[PDB]
Image (cartoon, rainbow, N blue to C red; front, side, top):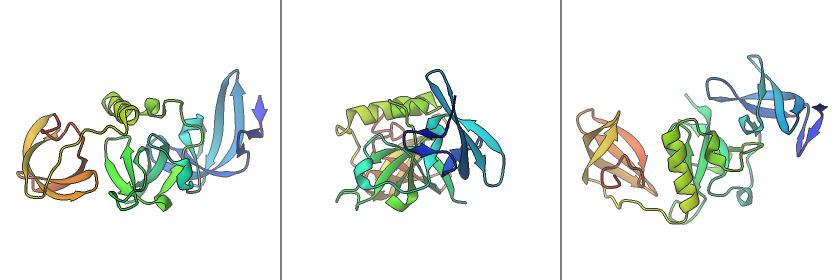
Length: 207
């Protein structure tokens, strides 16, 4: 069946859709199609083309109120070239994170963002992490979200020497900076930095 309405979605609304690049882009919802119990959403993007997308691959083009965001909420967020990329809410605003949202992006990256940097996915899966492609990231997120608020983390201080994983091996590294539940690691040989979640198994003390 072709529908005009489905939940709070309405044909002709402006929306965000996930392109094959895995980045998300502005478009118009031009059809809603059902095949038995399944639903698909046809989006005409502003620049490039039409896609027929599942409901977990479209997002509303507004910022959600804080009371609709939980740990485990499926979102699209500003990713640092600024793109929109999918992720999971790991923390909501509190004193210890200076009232920011912590996002775990689908590729394993973590960042603090503000409400104005977030968009809600329209039809998230019941287990929101189940559409994370990478099995290792998917399993990590499942454990994190379901164990929350029980969060094993390593206490780290600037100047501390540790081993950090990159491309499957351990590297000598130094803590450069700490920000909430994130640590900025300097890889000593490569002399570049990366922000990493303090409960990541990439930090040798967590492994």
